[PDB]
Amino acid sequence: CFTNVYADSFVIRGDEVRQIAPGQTGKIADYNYKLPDDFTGCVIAWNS
Amino acid sequence: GAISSVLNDILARLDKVEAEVQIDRLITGRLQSLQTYVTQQLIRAAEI
């Protein structure tokens, strides 16, 4: 059970989907959408 | 087992999270060294 579900959503080229991981550095994880080194969460993704 | 014992040469070349693979070692072997001086001084004190 969780105190809340927050879901973050966007669309990105596949070269950058890897940046959707905890503490990731680099352009999209640094200035677009960002996960901490402790991200107590998940990423769900497909080619669209 | 880690790469350097002066701290910034690591901070300058790695992220915030392989940090938790390369600063912690130094912290651990340091903590162990303090744990040896303090126990060895705590035995030493009983001679005195």
Image: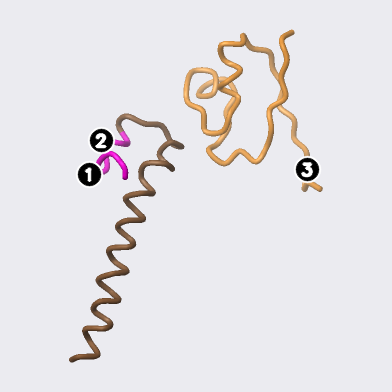
Q: Is residue B4 magenta?
A: yes
In the rendered image, residue B27, in percent from the top left (x then y), is placed at 34, 53
> Based on the displayed image, in which of its 4 quarters is residue B1 positioned?
top left
Q: What stretch is highlighted in magenta?
A: B1-11
**Majority secondary structure in the magenta region:** loop
The residue under label 3 is which amino acid type? Asn
Question: Residue A17 vs residue A26: left or right?
Answer: right
- Please identify, in this view, whether the residue under mark 1 or under mark 3 is nearer the observer: 1
Which residue is identified by label 1? B6
**Type of the residue with mark 2:** Asp
Separation of disc 1 and disc 3 at Cα? 42 Å
Mark 1, Cα crowd under 10 Å, few <14 / some 14-19 / many 20+, is: few
Name the element at disc 3.
loop
Q: Which of marks 2 and 3 is in front?
A: 2
Residue B15 sits above or below residue B43 on the image: above
* Chain letter for mark 1: B
Residues at circles 1 and 3 in contact by the CB criterion of under 8 Å: no
| Real-space CA distance between mark 2 and mark 3, rounded to the nearest whole angstrom | 40 Å
Q: Which of B6 and A11 is in front in this view?
A: B6
Q: How many marks?
A: 3
How far is disc 2 from disc 1 in space, using C-alphas?
7 Å
Other residues around mark 2 within 10 Å, as few (<14) / some (14–19) / many (≥20):
few
Residue A48 position (above or below residue B46): above
Chain A: give its colour.
orange
Report the residue marked by disc 2: B9
**Chain B painted colour:** brown
Give the percent coordinates (x, y) of residue A15: 56, 11
Residue at which label 3 appears: A4
- Mark 3, other Cα within 10 Å: few <14 / some 14–19 / many ≥20: few
